[PDB]
Structures are given as C-alpha cells and as structure tokens.
Amino acid sequence: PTVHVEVHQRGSSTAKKEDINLSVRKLLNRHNIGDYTWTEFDEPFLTRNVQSVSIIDDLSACTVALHIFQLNEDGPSSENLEEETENIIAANHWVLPAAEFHGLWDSLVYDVEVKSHLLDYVMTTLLFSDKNVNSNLITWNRVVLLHGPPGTGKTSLCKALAQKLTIRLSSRYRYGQLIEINSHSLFSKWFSESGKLVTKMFQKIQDLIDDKDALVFVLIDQVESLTAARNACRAGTEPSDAIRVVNAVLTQIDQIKRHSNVVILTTSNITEKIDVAFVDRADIKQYIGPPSAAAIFKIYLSCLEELMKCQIIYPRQQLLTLRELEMIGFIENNVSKLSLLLNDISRKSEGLSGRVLRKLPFLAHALYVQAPTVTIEGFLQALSLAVDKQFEERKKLA
Amino acid sequence: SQVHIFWTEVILHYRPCESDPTQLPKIAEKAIQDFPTRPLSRFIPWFPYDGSKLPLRPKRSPP
Amino acid sequence: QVHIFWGAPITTEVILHYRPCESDPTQLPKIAEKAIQDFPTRPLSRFIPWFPYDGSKLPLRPKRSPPAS
Amino acid sequence: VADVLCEFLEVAVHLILYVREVYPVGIFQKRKKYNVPVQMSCHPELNQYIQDTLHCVKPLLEKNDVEKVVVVILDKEHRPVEKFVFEITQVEQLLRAFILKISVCDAVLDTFTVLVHKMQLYVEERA
Amino acid sequence: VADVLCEFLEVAVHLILYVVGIFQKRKKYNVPVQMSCHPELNQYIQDTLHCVKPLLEKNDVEKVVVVILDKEHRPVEKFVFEITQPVEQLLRAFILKISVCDAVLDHNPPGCTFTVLVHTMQLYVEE
Ligand SMILES: Nc1ncnc2c1ncn2[C@@H]1O[C@H](COP(=O)(O)OP(=O)(O)OP(O)(O)=S)[C@@H](O)[C@H]1O
C-alpha cells in the first residue's frame, strides 16, 4: 500500500529540505496513530519552519512518503502580443504551486470519483514515460475534457488538479506552469487573423514547454468557442472562422503531443456545437454533474463547521455526519435533531448548482439573521427559508 | 558598520561552488542580526573546601 | 573575483555585495549567476555605406537661403 | 586617477542608459557640472548610487582581481541582454572617444547591473 | 599580529565545530587539539580567515562572529566573538573560556553547519 503526507513550509522559513523531511518523519514515528491534519507542534525549529501537516487518502503504519511544497506568493503574469502588445493575447500565467489555489482541492465535493481517475491518469502517464515505451506504438493526446451544467465547478477541478500535481510531483519537476487561455480575446475577426493569432500563443506555449524541467498545464476555458462545429453547420456564410481557426488549433495541439511534460485541460459547457474532430483528441472527457443529496449535505457541513471554526455559530454543537445517522438508524434525540433538519434541507435544496450552494449561507445570514453571533437551529432555519427564497427568485426572473 | 556572510553596507560572499541553497540572500540576512543573549552567569562551585575536614589518602604508589 | 551588485531600483569565487534594507529580493544569487554567465555572443558587426556618393548620380537643390542671424 | 575614472564610468553607465531608452522618463539633460562635457543623470540619488557602487568596488577594482567591468543592461527577467564589457587595462581624448565609442558601438545595436568579473568596450548582445 | 590572530580564529572556528569520530588529535601552535583531518575544510577555513585578512588590514573591525548555526540555518544558537580588535596558557585561556561557555551552555546537532561572519580577546554567546 501507500499513503501520502503533505506539509506546508513557510516562505519565511528557509531550512534545508532534508532537515524538514527528517523532522516530520520524527513527528510521525513518535505519534504514529484517520485523515486528520496536524496543526500543533512541539519543537521551536519545527514551529518557525512549518505551518501544518496533513494526511491525504489512525493507522500506525510506516508506508509514508513526504511531499513538501511552497505556494508561490505573487499571482498571475500577463501575456500580450509581441508587436501588438495592447490586448491581442492577454493570457494568464500561474507559477505553481500558487497561493490562491490552496484548500481548493479539499473543498470540492463530487460523487463520481473524478479526483482519483483524473490524478492516476497523470501517474500512469509518468510511469509509461519513465519505462521508455514506443511512443510510435502506444500514445496519448494529453488532452482532458470536462463538460457539464453551468456553475457546477467544472473549471474549479482543473486548478485543483494543477495544484495537487505540482505538489505531489515535487523533486521530479522543480515547479509547474499553468497557462490560462482566454478563448474570447483571440477572435480578432477580419479574414483569418484569429486563426493566425492562435499560432503566436501556441509558440509561447512551446517556449514554456521546452524548459524540460517544469511541468506545464494549459487550461482552456470555453473550448466550444475556439472549436466551433464546422461540418453539421449548414452555414457557408461563415467565411474562415469555422474552418481556419479550428484547423489552426487541431495542429498546434497535435504538435505538443510528442512532448511529455505538458497536459491540456479543457472546460466546456455545450456538449454539441463542438468539432467531432476534437472529441477524439481528448483522453478523458469527464462530466461534472450538479450536486446530489449526500454531496449537498457534505457541502453544507463544510460551510457550517467553517462558520463554527470562525465562531459565527458560537454554541458549538456536534454536527453528525450522514454515516453516524445511518449507524443510529435515524433516531430522534436531543443532539441528533439538527443533523436531521440539515438532511431535510438537503432534499429540499436539491438540483441547485454548487455555486449557489456555496452562496446560500451568505444570504441566509444576510437577510434573515442580522445577529453578529447566532445560535444553531435559527441559522439552520434561515437556510431552510433562504433556499425557498432562491427558488422564488429564480422563478421571478422567468 | 559592515557585515560579511561567508556562506550597514553588507559585503556578502558566495563561493559559487556551494550553490545548492536555491534562496541564498534571505538566508544571508538572518545570520547578521543580534538577538537576546542570556547573562554570562558568574559561576560558583557548590561544595567548597572546609579546612576543618581532612580527606582520604591510600598508601600505595605506582611501580 | 566577480562583483554582482543587484540593485538600481525601478576556480573563481564570487564577492557579491548584499547591502540590504529591504530583505525581499528572494533572488540575488541565481540572477547573480545569471549576470555572471556569458550568453550567445553576437559578433561585432561592421559598418558600411550602402548608398555611396556616386559621381554619375547627382543631387537636387532648392533655391532660397535661410534667414541669417 | 581612479577617483575620476570612476566618474568616467558614471558617464558611461548613464549614457548607455540614456541612448538605450531603458526608461521613458527623460530626466537626462546636458550637464557640464564642473566643466565635464558629459550627460549624467539629474537624480542625486542615482549620482550617489553610482558613487557608492564605485566606492564599494574601490577596495575591489584597483586590487586588480578585475578581469572585465561588465555593465550589464538587465532585462524584464533581469537577463544580461547587453553586456557592455570594459577591459580593465588603463586627458579627455579617451573620454570623448569612449563616448564616441559607445555611440558608434550603439550604432549597430538597437535596468542595469554593474558586475565586475585600450578600453576596448565590446557589446555581448543577444543575436 | 593580525595574521596570527587569524590563525587563532582558525583554531577557534574549527575546534568549536568540535567544542564525532571524523575528528583527530594533532599539533597546532604547540598544543594537541582534537579537530578534523579534512583538507578541504582546512583550506576552506584558511580561505575564510585569509579573506578576513585584508579586512583586518583595513584595521576597522568590531567582531568575528562565528555563528554556530542550527541545522535550520535559523539561529537557535550563535557564538558572537566581540574581540575589541584595535606563553601558551593564554593562547589556551581563550579556548578554556569557550569550553566553559559550552560547559554551562550546550552545543548543537553534530553538523553545526556554521557560517563565519565579521562585523567591521573576549566573547560571549547569544543562545
Ligand atoms: N460541486 C461542487 N462542490 C463543491 N463546491 C463547488 C462545486 N461546484 C462548485 N463549487 C464552488 O464553486 C466555485 C466556483 O466554481 P466554478 O468552477 O467557477 O464553476 P464553473 O464550473 O467554472 O462554471 P463555469 O463553467 O466556469 S460557468 C468554487 O468556489 C467551488 O468551490
């Protein structure tokens, strides 16, 4: 077997890597007790040179591997044209691991096991790379598609992937680059100038790829915009946008397929209206669906123990997870009532997009309760009314 | 007035052969500063010599 | 000896000069080892006229004179 | 004499900065301050900046470990795109000449760090 | 005397790296001290003191701060040596002051990874 451990090193901490590894291994072997995360330490060095330690899926086993990472402080660099520096490309450039991305991989909650599939995909990619397999004989396009309902966190999973991969695979690539492509600023449309513009940003991608000691992730938002369905569209009125801008990207991406330290990640909204010659050039086209009842309950939990962690809900009552309610078998009791009422909200708040789910506490603490400090079961009631407030508001805008 | 970091207008020192420590200059800053010293304790033996008491001497000598 | 003064605000050993009051460069040495290394050196190109003064191709000239002072 | 050859290097560094348009702030203007026909900077912060950089290479230059005064013009990545290299093997005749040199040297050509590894100024420039 | 003071700083820095089996008794300055046989470290400490040498030729100096680092390079200990720089017992008296200092106090992990500093016979320790 194997288990993974990740430890936040402070930027103002500068001790050597192997000392950090030895110290964390010492803490683990002394403690050696589930998936909980350490925050409390007992060594002045380790305190001033560590922020937290965490286990990612209660056992005293010693099959432990350490990944140590530094979330880079500064945000995005910008990419503009070479001689038309005003606005032509304007691509976003994250130098991973990055600060604004942490905690993101944990918060997201799905029910189709996208995380494991879409992570061990890259793991098997590296395995086949190091074993020297005949790239002429077994190959992959290094393109992963994610499509589904709007606001359901489709694109969130790609930044989480990139963060988790530049963290997990440290000391195998010093760092990673993540290029966020704006598929709306590359449509300067007068007689195939956009189809010529894709070329420049892809040469810059080549520039960031040849640095063979950096793992690069190219994240394309709205991959339906760049690749419009040319065949079924019975519109000859499309002069050269539907034929000389999709064909200007189906080549530059078949050109980076030969390299190995690149991965293409794409986010789509419309399943149709996309070129059939691009739904073959993607290894994984995984569908991100709207949250389901258990998922909704887990997200609502995350929110509520987040509020309790910041003391918003001052009287701390144990919120019982759905597994404990199944174990007891749905028995009403003086503490078990709150979880039950949460679960009734979960069925009643079914079918909403994850973004409004992660908003709903904001509104429920906005209009219905002005209290700077709130007791539970009134805040819960505020949620149970704010959800119906959201249904009626959606019905209001027709 | 000047401090050197053999790793105020500061004259650091680099010795390019050693250059594993990816971030050097911030390491160099730490080495310079002062920080709270503990007092140099004026020391005292705890069990002093009382002249009214006489110690023990065995007879034998080395060959 | 090589003397890499990172600054101007917007075997051989290295006597770099730190001289800090900011403590936030986070990269003197690699940039110092960047400024130290010689990079693709373009050869010194040579100068020459491309339109010489032809005795068979002669210039134009307007009439009037400038206001003297 | 190095106490005024340092100021000659001052002349050099600011004139390179000036002709390269490394900044759009046109602060530079003709300055014969103390009868020196050279075009320095009007930032006393930067005049004393060159002054004390040369001050802290004064226990360092005439010690003659010097193998080339490489006034790098840095880059956006802080890269030596144009290493203006001056060989340390030492009377206005050179000065204007160096001035001349610099200009005619920028002739072919199109953020500075003063690294110190016939004043045969040569430019190692990106191809 | 600055030269022999620098050799006594050698004695200090490295014997205090001692004050484990990779170390050995040998005759230095007519006393037997149990240091390291490392020739790389021998010439490296010689280089540290002989770059400190022109520094003391300046004669402007305050301390020779032989910082005994922790493994973190973030001092949990230190050894400032504030000699106010302008027979064998006293050339050994300094060593007995430092031994009694590390006596009442304590050392650091085996590899002390120390980085000698200078601020340009008496001492103490900022623990
Ligand atoms: N399924 C989910 N589970 C938990 N959190 C979610 C989920 N989906 C979305 N979120 C939250 O939604 C916020 C942003 O989601 P987005 O990824 O921007 O949605 P999106 O899918 O990008 O929609 P598009 O395609 O860009 S309209 C993040 O803060 C996520 O935490």
Image: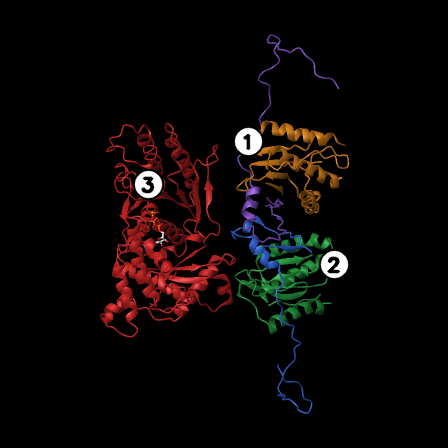
Chain colours: A red, B blue, C purple, D orange, E green
Subunit of label 1 = C
Between tags 1 and 3, which lies in front? 3
Instruction: Identify the residue position indicated by label 3 in the image.
Output: A223
**SS at mark 3 in the image:** helix
- Report whether residue E39 is seen: no
Residue located 27% across and 61% down the image: A346
Displayed quadrant of residue C2: top right
Subunit of label 3 = A
User: Which part of the image, by quadrant, shows the C terminus of chain E?
Assistant: bottom right
Name the foreground residue: B32 vs A310: A310
As shown in the figure, which amino acid type bears the numbered disc 2? Answer: Val
Residue located 57% across and 26% down the image: C45
Q: CA distance from mark 1 to mark 3?
A: 42 Å
**SS at mark 2 in the image:** loop
Labels 3 and 2 share a subunit: no
Around disc 2, counting alpha carbons within 10 Å, would you say few (fewer than 14), some (14 to 19), or many (20 or more)? few
Position of residue E85 relative to residue A332, above or below, is above
Between tags 3 and 2, which lies in front? 3
Give me the disc on residue C42. Answer: 1
Marks 1 and 2: in contact by CB < 8 Å?
Answer: no
Residue A114 image point, x, y percent? 29, 52
Between tags 2 and 1, which lies in front? 1
Displayed quadrant of residue A179: top left
Name the foreground residue: A278 vs B58: A278
Residue A62 image point, x, y percent? 36, 64
Q: CA distance from mark 2 to mark 1?
A: 51 Å
As shown in the figure, which amino acid type bears the numbered disc 1? Answer: Arg
Give me the disc on residue E1. Answer: 2
As shown in the figure, which amino acid type bears the numbered disc 3? Answer: Val
Labels 1 and 3 share a subunit: no
